[PDB]
């Protein structure tokens, strides 16, 4: 009833990486290592790096799923709010209910779990291009953390799983996400509160 969020590098040394985008008030996506938390604007590009120590087998995939961070909400499926699920901002592939989309990858698949009813988006695990040491997936988050009737100000985590071709676990990592109007200011504020 609750997906695991335990960090697990596995046999391939799987882990995420994030750019260093800063906290200017204009920034659209920014990652806080101190908070392990990504702050982003609605529907803007969120680059997430995938790092491995060795190449996983052909057919390996990478899945993203959101859960509520607070235990008392963790069994509730994270979905878009009653407004956003109806705003016809379809990209042609993502169901309108799904919070997390993958940008610019026609091989992305969206799953509505027949048992848990949770949403996820999965793509094939690509090898780095020549001259590159990692691969990057571009995610979009399609509701604000504040959306009423949806996340409703509750924080979420995104869980990224490296999977084999059967969907078995190879690796796992995660990060908190806040989708908000001013990620730079909010990151600064929360890092200050932590200090
Ligand atoms: Zn919304």
Image (cartoon, rainbow, N blue to C red):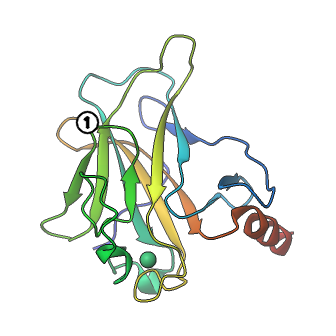
Nearer to the camera, 112 or 76: 112
Q: Compared to 102, does 193 lie above or below?
A: below
Question: Is 18 left, or right, of 75 in this rendering?
Answer: right
Q: Compared to 105, does 34 lie above or below?
A: below
As drawn, the residue found furthest toward the left would be 114
What percent of the width, then of the height, locates residue 192?
Answer: 85, 70
Q: Compared to 80, does 48 lie above or below?
A: above
What percent of the width, then of the height, locates residue 66?
Answer: 41, 64
Query: Residue shown at 70%/67% (left/top)?
Result: 182
Question: Is 183 left, or right, of 106 in this rendering?
Answer: right
Quarter occupied by the C terminus: bottom right
Secondary structure beneath label 1: loop
Nearer to the camera, 193 or 26: 26
The quarter holding residue 27 reads bottom right
Ligand 1, what quadrant?
A: bottom left
The quarter holding residue 153 reads bottom right
Query: Residue shown at 26%/22% (left/top)?
Result: 58
As drawn, the residue found furthest toward the front would be 88
Mark 1 crowdedness (10 Å alpha carbons): few <14, some 14-19, many ≥20: some
Query: Residue shown at 29%/76% (left/top)?
Result: 86
Query: Residue shown at 75%/64% (left/top)?
Result: 187
What percent of the width, then of the height, locates residue 95?
Answer: 24, 62
- Label 1 belongs to which residue? 164
As drawn, the residue found furthest toward the top would be 130
Question: Is 76 left, or right, of 180 in this rendering?
Answer: left
What percent of the width, then of the height, locates residue 147?
Answer: 48, 82
């Amino acid at each position: 009833s609750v997906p695991s969020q335990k960090t697990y590098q596995g046999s391939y040394g799987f882990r995420l990486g994030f750019l260093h985008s800063g906290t200017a008030k204009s920034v659209t996506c920014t990652y806080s290592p101190a908070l392990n938390k990504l702050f982003c604007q609605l529907a803007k590009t969120c680059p997430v790096q995938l790092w491995v120590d060795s190449t996983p087998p052909p057919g390996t995939r990478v899945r993203a799923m959101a859960i509520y961070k607070q235990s008392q909400h963790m069994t509730e499926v994270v979905r878009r709010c009653p407004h956003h699920e109806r705003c016809s901002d379809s990209d042609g592939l993502a169901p309108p209910q799904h919070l997390i989309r993958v940008e610019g990858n026609l091989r992305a698949e969206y799953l509505d779990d027949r048992n848990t009813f949770r949403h996820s988006v999965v793509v094939p695990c690509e090898p780095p291009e020549v001259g590159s040491d990692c691969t990057t997936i571009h995610y979009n988050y399609m509701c604000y953390s504040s959306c009423m009737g949806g996340m409703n100000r509750r924080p979420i985590l995104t869980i990224i799983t490296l999977e084999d071709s059967s969907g078995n676990l190879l690796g796992r990592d995660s990060f908190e996400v806040r989708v908000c109007a001013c990620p730079g200011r909010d990151r600064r504020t929360e890092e200050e509160n932590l200090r």
